[PDB]
Length: 107
Image (cartoon, rainbow, N blue to C red; front, side):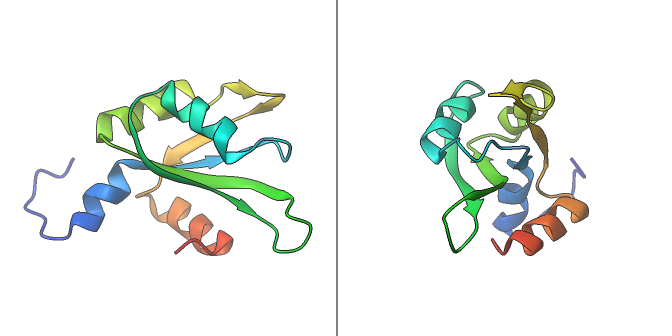
């Protein structure tokens, strides 16, 4: 990306992570797992839900094993209908999407 030396590995992790939205409340993390695996190898992922009934908020994130694989998700999954809801997949490293993660309370 920048082409600069980075000592913080969290930067590369953020770059290879994406922010996923428009997730059906009927969808599970296991269903999302499959959706993510269609793109490529995955490190981690989470679906954020309301701490009450358990109903998903429809937002989460996915960490891929490669930054280009994460970009492939942004290419493929972003705008792709998932059980009625067209998924939004952005770069988690983006300030806006990080603030969205803060709103979700993921860190």
